[PDB]
Image (cartoon, rainbow over all chains, first blue to last red; front, top):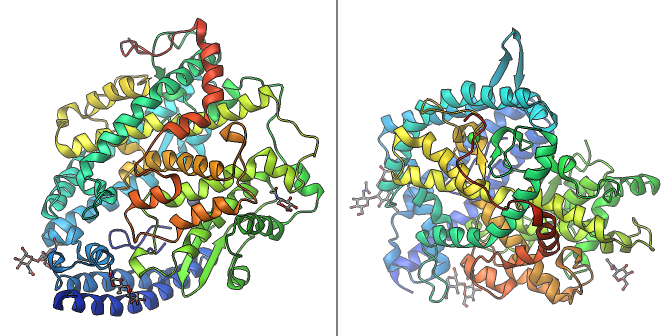
Length: 13
Length: 590
Ligand SMILES: *[C@@H]1O[C@H](CO[C@@H]2O[C@@H](C)[C@@H](O)[C@@H](O)[C@@H]2O)[C@@H](O[C@@H]2O[C@H](CO)[C@@H](O)[C@H](O)[C@H]2NC(C)=O)[C@H](O)[C@H]1NC(C)=O
Ligand SMILES: *[C@@H]1O[C@H](CO)[C@@H](O[C@@H]2O[C@H](CO)[C@@H](O)[C@H](O)[C@H]2NC(C)=O)[C@H](O)[C@H]1NC(C)=O
Ligand SMILES: *[C@@H]1O[C@H](CO)[C@@H](O)[C@H](O)[C@H]1NC(C)=O
Ligand SMILES: [Cl-]
Ligand SMILES: [Zn+2]
């Protein structure tokens, strides 16, 4: 999962 | 208005245009894999992840050219704040390499964790589904104890030396980013500065969590005492009437939720809970009908329809994890392997609530297209399913008989089931995060990590380890969020927010009667109140955004207590011949 965040841009699927 | 500020706005305009283009392309690679899991889609996903994360690192380098002290536009400050954070870049290449190795190893240990039969080493169980099934449905004290202990000795003991080094490296990263420690770094998600009347300090979060926990302790103690009495019937001779609950008898691997204790604690078991799944199949409902009903619900409070692109691009039937997608450029989608059940009817209302939130703040700058803080998005989703599951709502859309009347005992059963999930997890969530915060602060020495963990479990949670655990164990790391480096206090703040939201929306809807029966449907005043916060995204302090809905600037647990007041009254009467509270002295093994 991609996110609008600079601390956690990618989250595991 | 200054040269640095004007140059800052121009940079953000370029950043926002580039971020929108690359994030949309990345999101498509994410949608394609999650809907069509193939190696071609895995590789494009893997490539998109490196492109997306490298881009943000370069833009973070460019963002350092604009000092915050010379910026006066808060909306510009907020985006520069997010871009300028260095993260693990502050570490030497050696330490960041070591930290990444440790992080990946802990995650791999957790997800490959398996325990095998002592008398048959080829027969092994993973957490899902094997150990979880035992922890939910076993009435065998020793089988549950074997599952609970084997998980902590096989997985948790592996994680223990890694977690110690993870703490040292994370604290180093945090201090180099001008935080006190990693816990302080995490609490920055709630920080607000430079807005008079709305500021919120990182230390204030600890105070508010502790103060609200004090106010919920009477309700939890009464829930705990009722559950303890029912558990004494379920596990005879293993539970003291004055003691904590043994940690392996709570319905899952950690006692995070008490949900699976419902069939052991149901107050009036001859009365069944509402399940309109039969009505849905008898009315030939399908997945399209469910989301159409959800769309009508949001439309009825003044909120807009789903986009035409939503219907054409969504996947509403058979990675089946229910998700709401905000890809940008007007593209909103829901991924759900929907079944014709009441559960998926409620989840559909939950996920479309995410989309309504996304659509409301779509005009904000790229980095401000987010929930006001980490607790807001799931609070918005939860209150949608609260309204949809009430008998008043199910009667309106004709899935419940028009003559239906919820009675004394069905209401108590529902509230108790809600409390086992919602209230049961609050002491668990607070105590776990408090232990991490103290460990990061350096207040718990390594040679006392497990001693203090179980002291806090006993005192705060009323839960006791069934067997003694020395410092070779790492019991916290046996939970996914701890070993995978995720903050946990969001589950506490989200829970308080959702009842604050619902109470305000129901007062705007002029609801009569107890909170738990309220339906906000057909209330345009409720939708207006809610939309006033939804549009803000992250462009205003969360204290201000919370005030737009509920009229108060801070977390408050009184709405949650009001929601469970009928249960609290019933529990007090139920418990009038039982002890309420627990002694931390008793243990199963002493
Ligand atoms: C973030 O760190 C930089 C320096 O780290 C380098 O630049 C980053 C953007 C990242 O790419 C790292 O991998 C780099 O190694 C800080 O820049 C320093 O700021 C101080 C201000 O007191 C200044 O005296 C130094 O000369 C700067 N050093 C360099 C190399 O430019 C920056 O302040 C950090 N930002 C924040 C918000 O903490
Ligand atoms: C911070 O800058 C933004 C622009 O990046 C300002 O928003 C604009 O304000 C002007 C004047 O009111 C409007 O004409 C524009 O439509 C707004 N949007 C854009 C994209 O330009 C914002 O007002 C500034 N903050 C403050 C406090 O003035
Ligand atoms: C909303 O009102 C309309 C007519 O005003 C009615 O048909 C519908 O059933 C109502 N919905 C709910 C959820 O009460
Ligand atoms: Cl534990
Ligand atoms: Zn959600």
